[PDB]
Structure formats: C-alpha cells, structure tokens
Length: 257
Length: 8
Ligand SMILES: *C(=O)C[C@@H](C(=O)O)c1ccccc1
Ligand SMILES: [Zn+2]
Image (cartoon, rainbow over all chains, first blue to last red):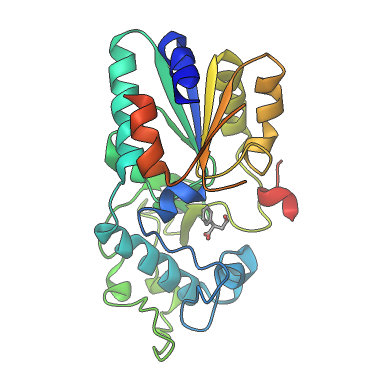
C-alpha cells in the first residue's frame, strides 16, 4: 500500500536507505557472477580474491580496469536520481537521508547523493599494499600500461604487465603496489564504517531496502535491530513490513516524490 | 570483522 507508506514517508525525520545489487543491475553494471557472466575465461569468484591478486596482479588489474572503464557508459538510473533528489530536498527541511550501499560503482555519487556509506568500497578508490593509504582515483586509464587493456572477449591475450608498471602509490618514498579499495571474497568489512552505519540505523525512523532484501546480507546485519525499535521497513525489489514489487527505477521515484 | 556474505 503506497498510500500507507507515504504517510510514514511524510513524517519520517531520518531515513536510511540500503541498496543492493539490483539497483546497479538496472544501470547495466556487469558483475560477472553466474549465468554466463564471464570475463574472458573467468568469473568474479576467481578474480575478486586476495589470492588471485597475489598470484596474478596484472590479470586482476585488467579485470578492475575493465570495470572502471565500462562505468563511463553506465549511467545512474531513476532510482539513484530519486534517492539523491530526495536527500537534497529533505536536507533543506532538516530531515536526514543516508544511503548504505553494497555497490562499488559510485552511481549514487554520480546521481548527486552526498551522505553515502560504501560498505564494500569503490572501483574508484585505491589502497596501497605497502603504506595502507586509501585514495580516490578516477583516472582513465589508471596507469599507462593498462591503456586499451581489460577487454572481456575470451580470445584476448593477457597483458602480462610487470608488477612495477601496475598502479603504484604516488608518495615518492613508498611506491607500493595499489589494489582496488574493494572488499573481496573472504575479506572483512571495515569496522569503522559498520560503527557509523549502526549509529545511522539506530537513529532512523524509516528504513528502505532497495534492490536486495531485509533477510539477506548485508541488510540482515542490521534490519532486525531496526525492526525491534518498531521502525517501518519498506522493500523495493523483484522478489517474493511494506514490499513494492518491480524494477526500482519504476517503483521508487513515485514513492519518494 | 564481518566477512562479506558471512563467508558463505
Ligand atoms: C563481492 O561482492 C565481490 C566484489 C567484486 O566483484 O569485486 C563485489 C563487491 C560489491 C559488489 C559487487 C562485487
Ligand atoms: Zn603507499
């Protein structure tokens, strides 16, 4: 019931919106998981691991370079936009909106959202393997050796880039190998981010779960905490307290206007 | 620390 949801929306002073893979899938963002979602001969399970990076950093960087570069042609969708406009509009009224996203593509930021927690990191951040520095990086290509590399076609040869020519840390003294600042399979979420998320979720008086569900990770980490405060939760997804079935780019903008 | 996907 959209009207009942909107009655809560009109009164809520602090909205937390959790976004999952569904909202990035509607922008056409490949993630390489499952049904013939291949990059050359591999899937994300093979590459998005510290062991793959340790064994073949050039191959893993080709894969991340490809992913960075495809984002030039993948755009924010109406769900991203509605969420950013809603944040701006409510902020002007002294009402707060925060986004907790599992997505690493920065589409929320390209849509105009400010208060965003990236629990899995970003394709457009690097972390230095040596000094640990995390930095924004949108450079195309990230390093000259990767220029024109990363093609997904199974026939493509490996670039076999020497490790010293992959992205390096720019502090002259350091020059460590950079890795994508993304949470890989088998790795832990950042505790500081989770603390901040918990504070937002404790404060919130309405919670939306978009392009994933309350019962799965990562929403399942916190959604019980919010439900037990008596706080309404509204789901927007394509799956079987409120639930709006369909593509988020159709359902969300009318709910948030 | 929390493993992504709970390690699953
Ligand atoms: C974990 O989810 C895998 C990781 C990746 O593919 O590098 C990822 C993180 C967040 C969203 C999609 C993929
Ligand atoms: Zn460094």
